[PDB]
Image: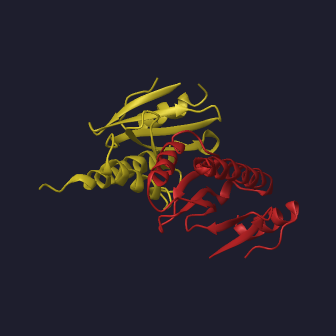
Chain colours: A red, B yellow
């Protein structure tokens, strides 16, 4: 119904600190996942996993990867890759109506986005892994 | 397919042809809207509304607009912009499980993707409107 009871049950089941506007939770000592209650009865999950180079070929390479990655399916909730307004931060986010959410599949969705984060962080970091 | 009756009721509700994998519907004599049954028991709407310049600074400006577009909510939240595998076509597309899809909310969605299509077509075309 409302997000707070579902988040409490979610936090209980997976053993996570309490959650509050929006709230955040640190995951695996590595990512900050944000939990936002939209206006139209949906819960958004968003995570910043990296950054785009400021300029040059490396920016363009990351930009071409960004643009194409959203064509295939990224995850549940219409998970999508994007760039924050500062032009630098790489973000994975999606939202789902709270009406169809309960603790179990909120838990599968949490594990899906963490999984996809790690894969995308890896892929973007591998653009600049060559040493001369 | 299991969702053919819903589509046929959605069409017939909206004065539209019946629909065939995937179906294509020509909308307002301007857009070819695709309906796809995904392998996730989901319905995917997709529309190609334009294309990125093949190369040069106008391509990069299109890529920058592409990467930022998906940070905001597009429509409700179940729509994202992407570049097609061919690297040219700009695509608006979103997924939703058939589970709760009814003819009513498939109508609100179908009007939303067409509306967002018109918005983003205009925005990308405004990248190249100055004449010297």
Left or right of B116 on screen, residue B93: right
Left or right of B24 on screen, residue B4: right
Q: Quadrant of the N terminus of chain A?
A: bottom right
Left or right of B120 on screen, residue A102: right
**Is A112 situated above or below B12?**
below
| Near-viewer residue (B82 or B26) | B82
Residue B105 image offset from top left, x and y in percent: 51, 48
Residue A86 image offset from top left, x and y in percent: 48, 69
Q: Residue at x 31, y 51 (%)?
A: B57
Number of callouts in the render?
0
| Near-viewer residue (B61 or B49) | B61
Q: Residue at x 30, y 50 (%)?
A: B58
Residue A100 image offset from top left, x and y in percent: 68, 53
The outermost residue toward the front is A132
| Near-viewer residue (A67 or A132) | A132
The outermost residue toward the left is B132
| Near-viewer residue (B84 or A73) | B84
Residue A49 image offset from top left, x and y in percent: 64, 59
Q: Residue at x 49, y 60 (%)?
A: B73
Dividing the picture into quarters, in which one does residue B69 lie? bottom left
Left or right of A107 on screen, residue B119: left
**Is B11 situated above or below A82?**
above
Q: Residue at x 26, y 55 (%)?
A: B126
């Amino acid at each position: 119904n409302t997000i707070q009871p579902l988040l409490d049950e979610f936090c209980r089941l997976n053993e996570l600190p309490p959650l509050i506007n929006r709230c955040q939770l640190l995951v695996d000592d590595r990512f900050v996942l944000y939990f936002t209650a939209t206006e139209d009865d949906a819960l958004m999950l968003s995570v910043a996993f990296g950054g785009l180079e400021k300029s040059g070929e490396l920016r363009v390479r990351g930009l071409e990867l960004l643009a194409r990655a959203n064509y295939q399916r990224v995850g549940s909730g219409n998970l999508a890759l994007s760039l924050a307004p500062n032009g630098r931060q790489l973000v994975l986010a999606g939202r789902q109506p709270t009406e169809h959410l309960n603790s179990a599949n909120l838990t599968v969705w949490f594990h899906e986005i963490i999984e996809q984060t790690e894969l995308w962080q890896a892929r973007f970091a591998m653009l600049d892994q060559d040493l001369s």
